[PDB]
């Protein structure tokens, strides 16, 4: 189930790259085992540098549920959330985060060195409380492979 | 002119709390002394926990200028930006940040203990690049007073 939803976030990353919507990033929000939102990076579609996949998923899931907190849902991210997205995950009060690729995989292919301390556990003023799971095995290999497979198929941002 | 745009952000904070749009926060984005966007927190109005003042202003300024980078623009925040909003400001490529009140001023009236390590220089992984100015003098006084004056008018969300 973790694997099913992480793979769907990865698939969203591929879809969004193929549509020219944005970069190779997807995110899926589920309530128990029911998909609430499934999104990819929309920075180029919306002309909106905040429209990362996680932020997009959070906005859509709060709209679908008519409330500004998601304490009963979990989020699956094809890549390690950046500082903006991890902050949005804190404010959204999602109860769990599962992510596939380490940020280093995205950095290696042209993106910024832009890593969230609170996620890695080196925050001082920003302390996370949500449960965090870095995928291993096949999930990790799938997520890491996204950046090799899409290496020169999208405009950087 | 720093004072002018900062007090415009303070007035946006008051306006939004009075319309019920969200909490007492405002942000103004400016391009060579021309105001590109003037917004306040819209979390309640939009049912969106990411719709802080700064993020909302970044969305609007980018839509207006037809680009995803505001490298020639500056942002005035009535209150010190939270981790999400500092992440957004970095992603937007804004040239300069000027903020009024320290985050403790918001926390004193019940807001989340939620401070951006990269803004205060306390991170291991996330470093900041942009010019940052904490206002002082009469601007800082008016900005800090917003939360004590506001207390009555909105319910913390
Ligand atoms: C969803 N999503 C995520 N998760 N990350 C992105 C995105 N766009 C650029 N990035 C970069 O990825 C690194 C962070 O890991 C940083 O360089 C960020 O700038 C994006 O849409
Ligand atoms: C614009 N804006 C800002 N700047 N901060 C906000 C907002 N809504 C809640 N907060 C809280 O303020 C502290 C951060 O300084 C944290 O407690 C945050 O949760 C908001 O819309
Ligand atoms: Zn992000
Ligand atoms: Zn914020």
Image (tube, coloured by chain):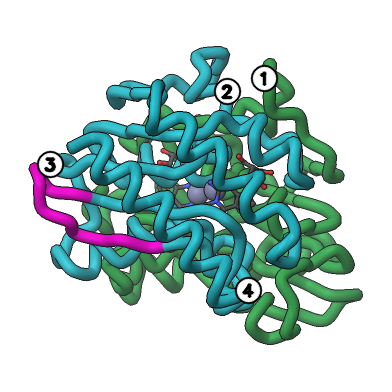
Chain colours: A cyan, B green
User: What residue is shown with label 2?
Assistant: A117
**Badge 4 is on which residue?**
A44
Where is the C terminus of chain A found, in terms of image quarters? bottom right
Residue A25 placement (x, y as % from top left): 52, 53
On screen, A79 above or below B2? above
Q: Position of residue B80 (x, y in %)?
A: 60, 43
Mark 1, residue position: B123
Mark 3–mark 2 Cα distance, whole angstroms, equals 24 Å
Q: Is residue B144 visible?
A: no
Q: Residue at x 31, y 46 (%)?
A: A92
Compared across the picture, whether B78 is left or right of A56 comes to: right
Image vertical order of residue A25 relative to residue A107, above or below: below
Q: Earlier in the sequence, mark 2 or mark 4?
A: 4
Mark identifier at residue A85: none
Q: Answer yes or no: is residue B103 visible.
A: yes
Discs 2 and 1 share one subunit = no
Q: Earlier in the sequence, mark 4 or mark 3?
A: 4
Are discs 1 and 4 both within one chain? no
The residue beneath circle 3 is: A72
Span of residues in magenta = A30-39
In the image, taking residue A61 as reference, residue B126 lies left or right, namely right
Q: In front: mark 2 or mark 1?
A: 2
Q: Is residue B99 magenta?
A: no
């Amino acid at each position: 189930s973790d694997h099913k939803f992480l793979t769907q976030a990865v698939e969203e990353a591929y879809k969004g790259v193929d549509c020219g919507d944005g970069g190779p990033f997807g995110a899926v929000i589920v309530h128990n085992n029911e998909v609430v939102a499934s999104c990819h990076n929309m920075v180029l579609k919306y002309t909106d540098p905040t429209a990362h996949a996680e932020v997009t998923a959070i906005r859509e899931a709060c709209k679908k549920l008519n409330k500004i907190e998601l304490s009963e849902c979990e989020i699956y991210a094809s890549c390690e959330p950046c500082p903006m997205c991890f902050g949005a995950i804190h404010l959204s009060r999602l109860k769990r985060l599962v992510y596939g690729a380490k940020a280093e995989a995205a950095i290696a292919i042209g993106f910024d060195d832009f890593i969230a301390d609170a996620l890695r556990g080196t925050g001082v003023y920003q302390k996370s409380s949500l449960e965090i799971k870095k995928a291993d095995g096949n999930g990790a290999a799938i997520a890491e492979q996204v950046f090799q497979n899409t290496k020169e198929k999208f405009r950087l941002y």
